[PDB]
Length: 169
Length: 55
View 1 (cartoon, rainbow over the protein chains, first blue to last red):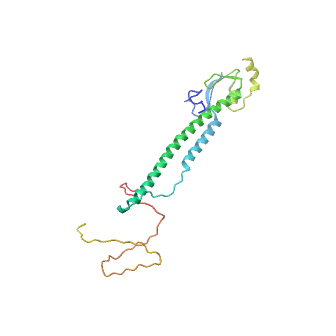
View 2: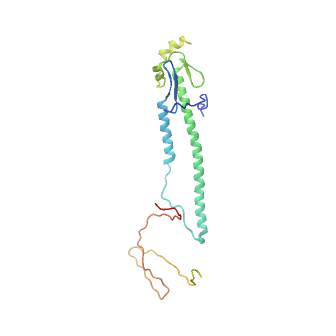
View 3: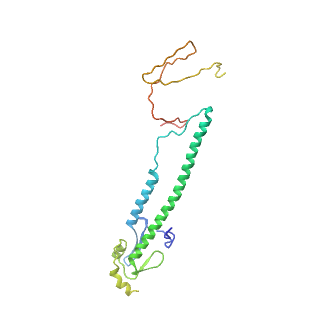
């Protein structure tokens, strides 16, 4: 558990439907939600592969479970009952435990993605912005739409607003 | 008495391979075949005891 979902970001966004993780920006030109295309796409692909691995790895053969035994073969019938119940027990335990573990893995995967996104933005901004606590950064300079889409792409330009941020600090 | 029958009738079955022959000898008490079933068998399956309709 990496302390993001329910951690330092205590809420989710319902107006954000284009992705799973992303940004909410407020500048002079406006405010809005935008998804992180790369992280969302990677997460979608990984979860799709996960579901397909859980489902399709199960191989089956043509089986005819169920046999008929007359009264003088109560031992073979009991053996068949034993075979059936053992398989049922094994498969029940395996299915329940696999789902229980895999749900954990998925939730921590999402938490990790949110935390990593936050870390990336933070290491891009350095001291040109400040961390207010709820997952937001207040810019010491003026970041317009171009600067914001630069942040949401990995192409921030710290030695372009370094002087303005130093003056406003 | 079962079905108002004091006597009984045992029923036997056999599978004859291609090229083989089946011989019946009898002084009495024999219910002879009238129809035989030429069959070629699959891998295997089951029997379902249900009242569900067939579609």
